[PDB]
Image: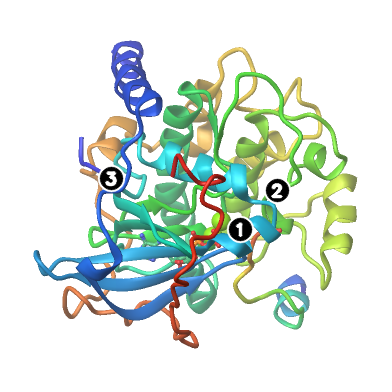
Amino acid sequence: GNAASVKEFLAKAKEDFLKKWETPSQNTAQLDQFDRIKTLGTGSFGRVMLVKHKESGNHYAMKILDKQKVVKLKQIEHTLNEKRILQAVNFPFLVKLEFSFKDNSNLYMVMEYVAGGEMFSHLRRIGRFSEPHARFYAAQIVLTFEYLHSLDLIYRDLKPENLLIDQQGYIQVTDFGFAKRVKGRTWTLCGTPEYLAPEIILSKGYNKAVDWWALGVLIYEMAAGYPPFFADQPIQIYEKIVSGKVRFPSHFSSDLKDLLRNLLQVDLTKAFGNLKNGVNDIKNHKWFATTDWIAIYQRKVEAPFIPKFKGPGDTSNFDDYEEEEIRVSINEKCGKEFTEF
Amino acid sequence: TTYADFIASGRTGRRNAI
Ligand SMILES: Nc1ncnc2c1ncn2[C@@H]1O[C@H](COP(=O)(O)OP(=O)(O)OP(=O)(O)O)[C@@H](O)[C@H]1O
Ligand SMILES: [Mg+2]
Ligand SMILES: [Mg+2]
């Protein structure tokens, strides 16, 4: 995202967001304006490829969604949410949507290419992050949720796989697939197993509190090297999540354990982020005592590590994926369903 | 150890959405 009182700042941010939310950008590029180079990653819904824009020579990350698959997996409204929200937001730690368009067969979202790779790859390779390292990333997520939640937005898919490291060593949140603008509670069963809050699993109405729960799981995983609740099958994971019992590694500081006990708390009346002081309860927690919040926002804090970059189109920080031809039918598919995309 | 149990589990690779 673009580089840099709180209430005043947020008021202006909401004004900017609403103008774009009410009148979304559309059809800002076309397929033949890019040369597709290689797949950077895939998920349950789309394929993200490194592409080069012909006229500018700039590299981007193009997310390709097969309309028919979107319908099959019942992600029509979710995908429309994804694009409408991403094109309207603006925060230092949110990936920027540069172009969006569609053709007979697919939907396309061209984002800034974040070359540092997924936090996931670095975390699994190194094993675990030191607490200062984990705290550096956590601070960026706390600020990002503060921003998103102020706009009545719930993210719903926080995980190392959806977090990218940029050239400066800072975080860039991607995959707004489950993002939604809602003022009340919502009920959709969505997210990723290890990060689902108890209320989602129990099919209960939930709110922004699930994002803070996810933050707790993310901090735990970053500092421990493994999730607080893991097993071989999702069902087994859900049973552990609902039990709520959490055990901490021997190296976790007392401050970190206290924070996690409050984030992964079953009592919503005591769960940090959803209390009277809201996000301030988190920002003022002892574990974040050394955190200079404004400096983080302004990206003035020294990053734990800067990813190795060889060139503008270097993809060495990403795994290799099997490639597939991107075909476009001569017949338009799901035209009316995605009219607003 | 918990770490050993995790590494021996079937979910140490990238996790896609439900
Ligand atoms: N802007 C980007 N720059 C670089 N790589 C990216 C970018 N956006 C996404 N990726 C990569 O592509 C992968 C797939 O994108 P994405 O997470 O949005 O797919 P998805 O289908 O929505 O996945 P999920 O199963 O989590 O819902 C990411 O995990 C990441 O590795
Ligand atoms: Mg994803
Ligand atoms: Mg997704």
Residue A103 image offset from top left, x and y in percent: 40, 60
- Which circle, 2 or 3, is nearer the viewer? 2
Q: Is residue A21 above or below residue A40?
A: above
Q: Earlier in the sequence, mark 1 or mark 2?
A: 1
Judging by the rendered image, the residue that carries numbered circle 2 is A190
Taking the view exactly as shown, the residue that stands out farthest to the front is A331
Label 1 CA crowd tier, 10 Å (few <14, some 14–19, many 20+):
many
Residue type of the residue flagged with mark 3 = Gly
Whole-percent x and y of residue A241?
82, 50
Q: Is residue A249 visible?
A: no
Residue A70: numbered disc: 1
Residue A1 numbered tag: 3
Ligand 1 has an atom within 8 Å of the beta carbon of the residue at disc 1: no
3D distance between C-alphas at marks 1 and 2: 14 Å
Label 1 chain ID: A
Q: Which quadrant holds the N terminus of chain A?
A: top left
**Badge 2 and badge 3 both on one subunit:** yes
Q: Quick one: which residue is furthest to the left in this view?
A: A56
Q: Quadrant of ligand 3?
A: bottom right
Marks 1 and 3, how far apart at CA: 27 Å
Up/down of A18 relative to A326, above or below: above
- The residue type indicated by label 2 comes to Cys
Disc 1 on helix, strand or loop?
helix
Residue drawn at the location 62% of the way across and 64% of the way down: A69
Label 3 CB, ligand 1: below 8 Å? no
Q: Position of residue A304 (x, y in %)?
A: 33, 60
Q: Is residue B16 left or right of residue A322?
A: right
Q: CA distance from mark 2 to mark 3?
A: 25 Å
Colour scheme shown: rainbow
